[PDB]
Image (cartoon, rainbow over all chains, first blue to last red; front, side, top):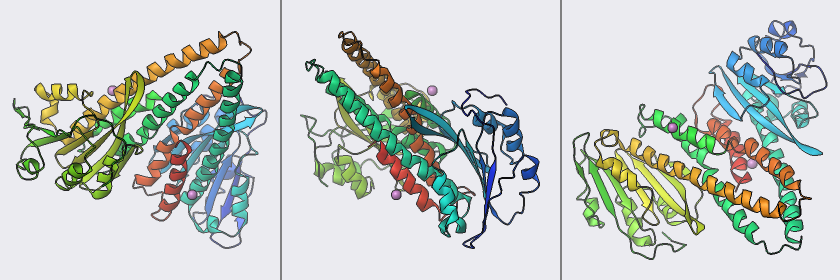
Amino acid sequence: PVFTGEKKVEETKITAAIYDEKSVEFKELEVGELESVVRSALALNKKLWIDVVGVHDESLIAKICEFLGIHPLAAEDILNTAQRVKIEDYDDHLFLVLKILLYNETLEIDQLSLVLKKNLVATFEEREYWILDSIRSRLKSGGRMRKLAGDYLAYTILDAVVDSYFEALLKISDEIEVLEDEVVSGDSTLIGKIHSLKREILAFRNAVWPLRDVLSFFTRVEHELIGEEVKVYYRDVYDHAVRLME
Amino acid sequence: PVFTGEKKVEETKITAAIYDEKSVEFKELEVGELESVVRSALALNKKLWIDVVGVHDESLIAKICEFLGIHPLAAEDILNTAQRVKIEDYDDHLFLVLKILLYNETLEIDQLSLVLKKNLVATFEEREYWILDSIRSRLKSGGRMRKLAGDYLAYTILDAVVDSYFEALLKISDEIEVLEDEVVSGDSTLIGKIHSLKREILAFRNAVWPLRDVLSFFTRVEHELIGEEVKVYYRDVYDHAVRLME
Ligand SMILES: [Co+2]
Ligand SMILES: [Co+2]
């Protein structure tokens, strides 16, 4: 359990929410400590979102994983802030590593680990003041949030995260437009090579971007057309594809 | 059955190969016409690779699909050269649209449809002189090519295609390096904004690139953790993700 890449200037703060159907209840006691979660937090009759807001303490989380049944191999990845975006079947929990794009003057990239077990969602954040603000607010209102399992919650987070990527992409395009300009507008209009290249990159994107998605079908879909022997081979092209854009 | 985007300067030429285990046989009669395939080509005891090398004729292929049991919806996509890279379960055949990157002076993008049914591989190419050259050569040699089903063949093609993407990516990087230079070396070294941006784009790539892959797990993997009711929601983030880079 080793941690690299300091990014908080604060100490860890666990916080958990409990919701029981459309019923107006949303009990969210911040009093999780480590012992204040393994025992007192059980009650296998309620919906729980454990929310960890500090990942510097390699001791705390290593045990927090133990106390939630989060496989070791995931736990070290939760600590490696520079992990690739992935998903893993564990198989009593789904573990995924995401990335958050923070335009704090310079673009900053934070990590957001997410864990889903049977009626249990464990998120792991670098900082706070996130986009999870409304995920609290949606748990505040008597909606489809409370009525539905952890699976729906995990979804809502992914939906919030993915929304913010349209923000970044928008800002990034302005930047290109602004740089492309002062290059071209920079009297050196003898450069229509920018757009020859621009089309080469986007042609590559369209070619290779959906590709990892295509190859992973053979890798994790039961089908009478791919024999359980040729799976080896498919996983390998998939690997080659993964590395293309790494 | 409508076709757009002319790119051949030649007429359609069907060609089929037949291989029966490690046995030194590799019967590949070009005499497929349309009637010379529906009937004579049956023999449900052999391994068949139908190889179509022209996609301009919306009449020919529409019936070629019929004669291979290739769903209509796929067949129109086989004709739409400007389709996105995709895969579909049909479910007696897998249908995928790929893209081939051809550095013929200017980068050129061709389409390569692929269809896999039970012991049957149907490819659909824009031009010839492809990378399929060795796929013939591998069928020529008494290897694991012949011994194994269509699933393995479909794989070998994907492996050849994916290999060629490392070629493009290599050439594209030179182009960037060369343009980045004559921009910077273009006396306007007052531009370290290139690398501020370069890191913003690559940070986006690392964030969003593996993402479509991550979201598609929930979409097409049977799992006791995602209920068969919340699938709707997941498919939707997936859709949002698909559009990000489209
Ligand atoms: Co390999
Ligand atoms: Co939507």
